[PDB]
DNA sequence: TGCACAGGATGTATATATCTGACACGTGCCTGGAGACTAGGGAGTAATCCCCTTGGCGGTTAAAACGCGGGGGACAGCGCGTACGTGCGTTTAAGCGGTGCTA
């Protein structure tokens, strides 16, 4: 979805596409490579009312 | 007899003045600004060709890092002996201003 990715694809810089492919493969192989699953926790309000 | 003071003597901190330096105001000349001529170095313009990262990636290696033993280097104490510090008396010539020459 990321527009910059689309732009990169449009560029046709063979290196850039190779890198994109590498990132895709990384994402498929195990998500931790692309982004560690964030450890979910409550939202914190700055100060009570 | 010895003291009080009437009459007189050197002195001097106080006070009035004379003996030296520095800054501002007056002359007057080698100027600083200005006018105009000047051109060629600076700056605006245009390639052009070459050198600098791409970008992370694995498979390696050479250098870096970390761990350990220990032994000897650094270093705080201190016994003591003397050679620099403080204080004379004493001498020299360094400082002061002066007179006459000159290079």
Image (cartoon, coloured by chain):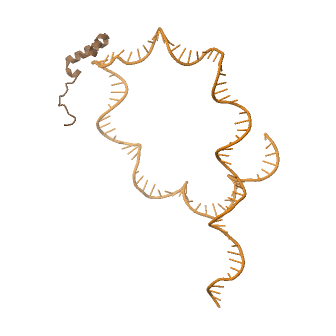
Chain colours: A brown, B orange
Say left or right for A12 vs B33. left
B101 vs B32: above or below: below
Q: In this orientation, which residue lies closer to the viewer: B80 or B55? A: B55
**How far across and down, in percent of the image, does residue B11 sit?**
68, 70
Count of numbered labels shown in the rendering: 0
- Which quarter of the rendered picture does the C terminus of chain A lie within? top left
Question: At 31% across and 11% down in the image, what residue appears?
Answer: A11
Question: At 29% across and 10% down in the image, what residue appears?
Answer: A10
- Write down the quadrant of residue A17 in the picture: top left
Q: In this orientation, which residue lies closer to the viewer: B55 or B65? A: B55
- Which quarter of the rendered picture does the N terminus of chain A lie within? top left
- Write down the quadrant of residue B12 in the picture: bottom right
Say left or right for B20 vs B52. right
A39 vs B44: above or below: below
Q: In this orientation, which residue lies closer to the viewer: B38 or B25? A: B25
A18 vs B8: above or below: above
- Write down the quadrant of residue B86 in the picture: bottom right
**How far across and down, in percent of the image, does residue B40 sit?**
61, 15
Q: In this orientation, which residue lies closer to the viewer: B82 or A38? A: A38
Say left or right for B38 vs A49. right
**How far across and down, in percent of the image, does residue B20 sit?**
70, 52
**How far across and down, in percent of the image, does residue B56 sit?**
30, 19
């Amino acid at each position: 979805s990321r527009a910059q990715t689309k732009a990169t694809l449009a560029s046709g810089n063979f290196m850039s596409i190779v890198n994109c492919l590498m990132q895709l493969r990384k994402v498929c192989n195990h998500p931790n490579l692309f982004e560690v699953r964030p450890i979910l926790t409550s939202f914190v309000l700055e100060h009570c009312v």
